[PDB]
């Protein structure tokens, strides 16, 4: 089968011809019908997230097929698989745990001590077929098609968990930083669909700000055209925002938005652009603000985003679909910030 | 009446003779029987917490009587006060809110927009008498004497709130940084009394480490005699700690202990030594750690620490009591780190 | 001023001429612009909730002006009131606490040991003016008019609290019993606006079922035309519902809907029709279901429903407005179940 | 191997000679070193819990080996088992789920749609060996011996979950009904070890009341010697208790203790004696009390009780150990209420 893999750090992904794996035990072989392209693949291709080298620091062994936003058709199942037939369309949660470690036992599968992350340290969906380590991480699609579903296995589940950690309610205001992108448009949608909170989206490109407006943001700010702090101060009447979901975490965002936090404000850190958080400690203490990291999601979150989307309450804003052979171009679009919403590969 | 007040920044507190206030409305005039000395008064005397000047940045108007760990006898009450008689011994929650702002309405009175903090921006207990803005912030002592009670209105309520925010349970390990001090000995006790969690206390003085051992810590480390990270790594079997309560937040603690956090670890920031938090953002995100500020406590927290102490489940470790005229010497002991547990003034 | 009061149990409310109270201290005199009519006033007029006599069992002292859904204009304030001017339009939370008891201290003011409930044990809004015990229980209207606001001080805040206690999320299904009524239409809206959960509304009148459909229910059932259990079984695919908000709690509802609960299901009991809950204990234990009572709401809940409505995310379905002199007729409509949505008096 | 099994309802358990199962896949064959005797086995032998027949209503297929408090030595593992060696001493969580259903995905394994409950619908520990469906449900003992550990797999995990659902804190009072029994002594211990709450234990036998006193109860009541309601009213100063953990749920307890609940009180229903809950609905609503069922525990709870016990913070009060051949006599002791604490079989 054809596969687009990360063969060498700092080089374009490589289109290779490799064998189709045989599913055994609880594994499932999925015929890929859609593979979302995440800005994380820009970092993968660069070989790192900040100063955390995927090889030396995270244990990633090259070559590896990328693609962790997964949706497809069941081709073959192992002997232990129960509840699926050939042809069934499913979304796949790629953040899998082995089930016995501390984190797996308390329902935090994605923080497993021996993680199996399809598209990161295990082969992903940028191919004709993909192996699912365990069938319990799949979701039978009922209303969604594969293209709409794929993005939910990362951008959806990640922002669903992030919106929950932001502890939002009708009396609060949320600020989404980088609201016009893949996760940004998703964070805005979920917050609109289930929190009742007022939403402010900020980006730095005309089309991105427009995308955030389309995603449902009550207020949108173009940080290139105006001072976002003055505007946020105006919108919240000097109270500041109760929560920020930063989908960048660059020196540009981290040196600005934490100052917009209200007392008890939660700064949810999702983006992986690679900067260092730097804030005066007494200021954190006196305002009781929090800086909380959020990583993809667990089985519970997956269930949550999939049911929300199946109900039509949220829907990935797919602005572009292209062939698997165009994986590098789709990634260049994110690296050059020439994309909005989400792009999906349709092998 | 005699009062020890902060008259000038960077100078010794001043013993003055001032008028005794007349309680009106819901106010209450308390005859001070005990006034705890907090390391925060070292910062007050220096005129700042980190680079946050108490005058220009926090609105503190000099002169102001210090002393926010309050316990005493009811001398006189206003016309609105209901439920107290002259002579009743009470502990006083000094972190008072006006009751109508957003934070007061959601039960976070210490984060009131118009805070009345006895000993900080309003006169405190380093005097013969002290005015209590509102009687609902008092607790009638049933078993505790004034000396034992006073420290609970700051070191107790603060660390009670911090231990709650650390989200501890029997499967977790807590690390208390500066465990031999006033708050340190209290954090260790509360965590021992109600979380079931394993406790590690770290300090840098032989007597402090011993105090932390006496407070109930399962493991104690003298960071002056050995590498605390190697030891914490050994105790937690390389898992790291699920929570840290840092009662320093100095460049020395912040550049070390965050590295000891396990995945999902919570770094509760209480200390006000004045450094800057600096940590690689991708590391925060990938391990889902959190840096959360905690400030004194609300009416709910107060109730919690007072009942815990009245039941004899925790008890401030008072290692020294002295006269009100000795306020500066007691503060010097904290500034020079020549104290353990808690010191209390007995006017 | 004119007032419609409960003078005698089992008799029509009485239109009387009484003196206008003078606001002192933190009290506020409100010129009533709208007074919602709640089915609770049907019980008040009958002198009881189930077998709990309002006089002998609850301490209600007759005569008392009814009306606890309050919205109006500030006429006069006491000496302590801060932040309001004559003419300001406000909604009033009638479930007031004195502020010092255990329940007031933990932010559950409606469960105060010495409750001041306007319209129940204190004079209410079925009059030209009404006294507000404490100004902190008011909310300044920004977008809502008085008629739209009034119902939020009971049907809104109550069902907001009930929807929160139902612990809903996108993977869950909520069942609202009596969904076409005043609270029913509100419960459905709030659940639609902030939980992401699938909603099933059930009633027994064609117009009520239609109202519930208009409120946003995904599925509606007329228990008079069909077996509600068979239908709920079909909709949830035999899983049952994760939560039920019963706005009746009659022998007719309690002997039916608890059987529709899924494992861990929460049966939120709001209605006061007066029956006895009867369920096999082993069944409760083995399926971990819960029967939880919910009563009006606290200051936090009030804030939540008011902000949700001001944002236009929910809006009371007012199906009828009439003059204060018509109070008895409006109550008869609820007693005879010849009403849907909410009725509001406009003195 | 020898096994004590439920062969016929209403008859004494039968000592049979059956084959030793062969562990395959993730299964594990454990050599039983201790098997706790639970009052649930009295109900099993009677063929029902209340009016819920274990055969017709729960799907239990006879014959079945009883015994769900499990601790033993690893004899043999399947091909998928990872992390264990022959001889390793482990405690076994018998409340196992298949891992794919809704409840398994949200971390509520014990509420699995296709439950595998060792000792209930699958063979248990009342034998020489026992098969563990999945190895991830085991806990490697480090400090506890098998006899001390076994009881934690039911009485411990169940009461750990129940104490957590009681939402206890230092300002609250807990009432344990049947506090001198197997679960009672455990509930009292855990509440003493991790809640900070004041504890009241009630029983009706002199030795049972004494056992509850030894378990750590602050107050003990013998309901045979005095009116428990008058005493509870006295202890709580008429406030009532914030939580009740009823380990009976008989007409005798259910018609008494709910009346002792404070406003917002939580009545946790654990016992399976078989009565019907009957309480006036308006009373539930007006006091916001809750009746919540609690069933054994999930993987998270198991981790919690095992770590609490390994730390020596709680310890089953084993008052009797006897041979496997004496299973019926041990059960008669519970059925006749001639036992306190916990009894363990040592095959
Ligand atoms: N924590 C997790 O589990 C997780 C999961 C998925 C992706 N991510 C990370 O999230 C980040 C975003 O991913 P994505 O797929 O949404 O990317 P994207 O390229 O679709 O969107 C990024 C957005 O950031 C905006 N942006 C750039 N500079 C900005 C500035 N100075 N201020 C405000 N906005 C700015 C862009 O205009 C763009 O709309 C990446 O670093 C990715 O690796 C994290
Ligand atoms: N956030 C809040 O609401 C709040 C409330 C009260 C106090 N505080 C702050 O908490 C801090 C501690 O106050 P306290 O009264 O306990 O002080 P303290 O002087 O009693 O104790 C401080 C402890 O820190 C230890 N220490 C010093 N250097 C150390 C190092 N490098 N590593 C480890 N331990 C070290 C000392 O030996 C001492 O035992 C102060 O900065 C104070 O202002 C904050
Ligand atoms: N717990 C609280 O704090 C609180 C607050 C407000 C009102 N209430 C109580 O809530 C109840 C409802 O009040 P409301 O103002 O919404 O009343 P309402 O008269 O507006 O609505 C009641 C609804 O119940 C429906 N109904 C009647 N019989 C039914 C049956 N057998 N099955 C299903 N639906 C049926 C009616 O058709 C109607 O739509 C009253 O008992 C009231 O006292 C409680
Ligand atoms: N929900 C669950 O998951 C779960 C788990 C284990 C056991 N259980 C159930 O818990 C119940 C208790 O089990 P156990 O093993 O502790 O039993 P046990 O026999 O050890 O203890 C029961 C206690 O109840 C006391 N008692 C009897 N009548 C009483 C009365 N009128 N008032 C107060 N106390 C009274 C006895 O004196 C005795 O100490 C059983 O019905 C059992 O099936 C439930
Ligand atoms: Zn991604
Ligand atoms: Zn794992
Ligand atoms: Zn202090
Ligand atoms: Zn305030
Ligand atoms: Zn009402
Ligand atoms: Zn009160
Ligand atoms: Zn049992
Ligand atoms: Zn299952």
Image: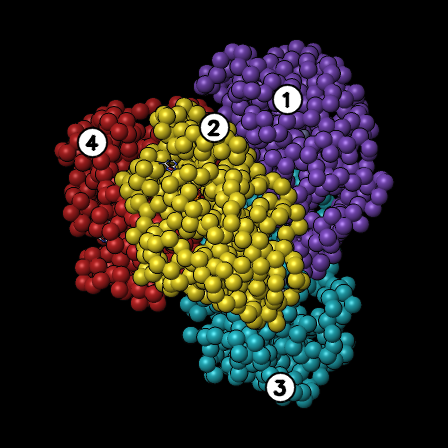
Chain colours: A cyan, B purple, C red, D yellow
Q: Count neighbours of disc 2 (C-alpha within 10 A) and say few if under 14, some if 14 to 19, many if 20 or more.
A: some
Figure quadrant of residue A334:
bottom right
Q: Position of residue D255 (x, y in %)?
A: 30, 37
Nearer the camera: disc 1 or disc 3 = 3
Report whether residue C156 is seen: no
SS at badge 1:
helix
Q: Verify CB contact (< 8 Å) between mark 2 and mark 4.
A: no
Is B172 left, or right, of C343 in this rendering? right
The structure residue drawn at horizontal position 81% and vertical position 27%, both measured from the top left corner, is B338
The mark closer to the camera, 3 or 4, is 3
In the picture, measured across the screen, residue D115 lies left or right of residue C248, that is right
Q: Which residue is mark 4?
A: C6
Which residue is labeled 3 in the image?
Answer: A20
CB under 8 Å between discs 4 and 1: no
Mark 1 crowd level (few <14, some 14–19, many ≥20, 10 Å Cα): many
Secondary structure category for the residue under label 3: loop
Both on one chain, marks 1 and 3? Answer: no
The foreground one among B205 and A310 is: B205
Q: Is residue C50 above or below residue A176?
A: above
- Residue D236 lies in quadrant: top left
Q: What is the spatial separation of the Cα atoms under label 2 and label 1, in whole angstroms?
A: 25 Å
- Judging from the image, mark 1 belongs to the subunit labelled B
The residue tagged 2 is D219
């Amino acid at each position: 089968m054809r596969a687009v893999r990360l063969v060498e750090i700092g080089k374009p992904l490589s289109l290779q011809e490799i064998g189709v794996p045989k599913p055994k035990g609880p594994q499932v072989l999925i015929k890929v019908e859609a593979a979302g392209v995440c800005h994380s693949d820009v970092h993968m291709r660069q070989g790192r997230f900040g100063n955390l080298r995927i090889v030396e620091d995270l244990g990633v062994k090259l070559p590896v097929t990328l693609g962790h936003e997964i949706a497809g058709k069941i081709e073959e199942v192992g002997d232990e698989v129960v509840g699926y037939s050939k042809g069934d369309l499913v979304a796949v949660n790629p953040w899998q745990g082995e089930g016995n470690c501390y984190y797996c036992r308390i329902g935090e599968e994605h923080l497993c001590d021996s993680p199996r992350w399809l598209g990161i340290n295990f082969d992903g969906a940028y191919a004709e077929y993909v192996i699912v380590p365990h069938y319990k991480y799949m979701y039978k699609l009922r209303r969604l098609n594969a293209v709409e579903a794929a993005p939910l296995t990362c951008s959806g589940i990640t922002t669903y968990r992030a919106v929950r950690k932001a502890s939002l309610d009708p009396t609060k205001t949320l600020l989404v930083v980088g609201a016009g992108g893949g996760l940004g448009t998703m964070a805005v949608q979920i917050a609109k669909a289930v929190s009742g909170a007022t939403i402010i989206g900020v980006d730095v490109r005309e089309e991105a700000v427009e995308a955030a407006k389309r995603a449902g943001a009550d207020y949108v700010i173009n940080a290139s055209m105006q001072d976002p702090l003055a505007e946020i101060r105006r919108i919240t009447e000097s109270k500041g925002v109760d929560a920020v979901i930063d989908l960048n975490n660059s020196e540009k965002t981290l040196s600005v938005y934490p100052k917009a936090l209200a007392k008890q404000g939660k700064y949810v850190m999702v983006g992986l652009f690679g900067a260092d958080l730097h804030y005066h400690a007494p200021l954190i203490t006196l305002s009781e603000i929090q800086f909380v990291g959020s990583l993809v999601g667990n089985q519970s979150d997956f269930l949550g985003i999939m049911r929300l989307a199946e109900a039509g309450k949220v829907k990935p804003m797919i602005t572009k679909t292209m062939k698997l052979e165009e994986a590098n171009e789709a990634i260049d679009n994110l690296e050059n910030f020439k994309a909005i919403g989400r792009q999906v590969l349709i092998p």
